[PDB]
């Protein structure tokens, strides 16, 4: 096993200016270390603290264009996570809100980017366990990143072997990648809407899966179906998913059928301490 020499930066509370509440608490704000203003998100009992420090550990250990980056922690009254602000929100809200504006090219490119980040996480021998459209953040419509590592080592995103046997592999992640692509292609529909979680186990054993989304050629829907094989080893590899969705993004409309187809500010992606 190789030593994890990731650095953990600890930040002064007086370096932040919380701008407003993003959700509840996670705030939006500016981090001023150097003549630079970094736009950031800021996540504010003993069990609670042990679980945010776990997230910092994972996030400080990853470095990839399609994974979310830690900027630091702050050790005040509670623990604060400081990450890069993704100004367009999570991808689930974004497809819901811009239903009538997403082109086939954007959808296929997101599937490539999410698969690229998952492939990176496999490189780093790391299992996400909570891949979902709600946990993919949008930096620009052109650039998305995987986030939320509270489970890194939800019934309706889990491989069947995870529901039955509490078994998680990179191939159980590919199953969740499958469900996540289906969220995108249905513009934010809820997987198994109405179906109570207690039932998901037996349904999947009976051979049923999520249905073909309307904009989806059989080419795209067959890739989702392959992510849902009961035999984990028969599921596609995250690196084959990159290849396949890449070839599709070269000709998006053959595969997705859609009607109508502040002065010293620096994105965290350009602050490379
Ligand atoms: C889908 C929920 C969401 O994330 N919405 C969101 C996110 C950001 N930017 C951002 N950047 C990095 C991390 C986070 C983050 C981490 N946990 C949470 C929890 C709640 C909200 C954000 C979180 N977020 C936005 O920047 C402007 C906006 C935004 N929106 C659109 C809020 C939508 N609902 C959830 C309030």
Image (cartoon, helix red, strand yellow):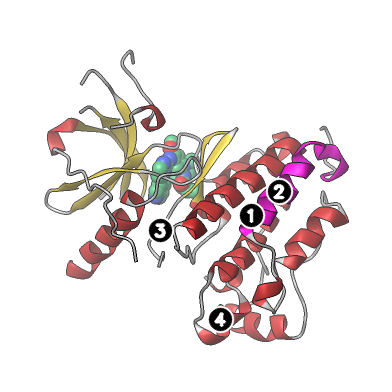
Residue 247 in the magenta stretch? The answer is: yes
Question: Of callouts 1 and 4, which one flags the residue occurring earlier in the amino acid sequence?
Answer: 4
Q: Residue furthest front?
A: 1
| Image position of 270 (left or right of 65) | left
Say what secondary structure mark 3 lies in. loop
The residues colored magenta run 238-256
Q: Residue 250: x percent and y percent? A: 78, 36
Magenta portion: prevailing SS class: helix
Say what secondary structure mark 2 lies in. helix
Depth check: give the residue in front, 163 or 235: 235
Q: Find residue 97 and name its label.
A: none
Q: Find residue 163 and name its label.
A: 4
* C-beta proximity under 8 Å, tags 1 and 2: yes
Q: Is mark 3 within 8 Å of ligand 1?
A: no
Q: Which residue is mark 1?
A: 239
Say what secondary structure mark 1 lies in. helix
| Rendered view: 70 above or below 200 | above
Quote the CA–CA distance across marks 1 and 2.
7 Å
Q: Residue 69: x percent and y percent? A: 38, 43
Instruction: State the residue at coordinates (34%, 20%).
Output: 265
Question: Of callouts 3 and 4, which one flags the residue occurring earlier in the amino acid sequence?
Answer: 3
Q: Which residue is mark 3?
A: 149
Residue 54 in the magenta stretch? The answer is: no
Q: Which residue is mark 2?
A: 243
Q: Residue 58: x percent and y percent? A: 34, 57
Quote the CA–CA distance across marks 3 and 4.
19 Å
Question: Of callouts 4 and 2, which one flags the residue occurring earlier in the amino acid sequence?
Answer: 4
Query: How many numbered marks appear?
Result: 4
Depth check: give the residue in front, 241 or 156: 241
């Amino acid at each position: 096993e190789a030593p994890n020499q990731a650095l953990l930066r600890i930040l002064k509370e007086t370096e932040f200016k919380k701008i407003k509440v993003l959700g509840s608490t996670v705030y939006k704000g500016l981090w001023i270390p150097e003549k630079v203003k970094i736009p950031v998100a800021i996540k504010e009992s003993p069990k609670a603290n042990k679980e945010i420090l776990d997230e910092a550990y994972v996030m400080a250990s990853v470095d990839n264009p399609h994974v979310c980056r830690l900027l630091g922690i702050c050790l005040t009254s509670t623990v604060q996570l400081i990450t890069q602000l993704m100004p367009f929100g999570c991808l689930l809200d974004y497809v819901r809100e811009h239903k009538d504006n997403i082109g086939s090219q954007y959808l296929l490119n997101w599937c490539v980017q999410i698969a690229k980040g998952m492939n990176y996480l496999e490189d780093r021998r790391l299992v996400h366990r909570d891949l979902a459209a709600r946990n993919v953040l949008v930096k620009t419509p052109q650039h998305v990143k995987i986030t939320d590592f509270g489970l890194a080592k939800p019934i309706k995103w889990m491989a069947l072997e995870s529901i039955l046997h509490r078994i998680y592999t990179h191939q159980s992640d590919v199953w969740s990648y499958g469900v996540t692509v289906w969220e995108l292609m249905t513009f934010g529909s809820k997987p198994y809407d109405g179906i109570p979680a207690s039932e998901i186990s037996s349904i999947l054993e009976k051979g049923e899966r999520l249905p073909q989304p309307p904009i989806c050629t059989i080419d795209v829907y067959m890739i989702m179906v392959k992510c849902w094989m009961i035999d984990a080893d028969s599921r596609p590899k995250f690196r084959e998913l990159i290849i396949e969705f890449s070839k599709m993004a070269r000709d998006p409309q053959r595969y997705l059928v859609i009607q109508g187809d502040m002065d010293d500010v620096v994105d965290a992606d350009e602050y490379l301490i």
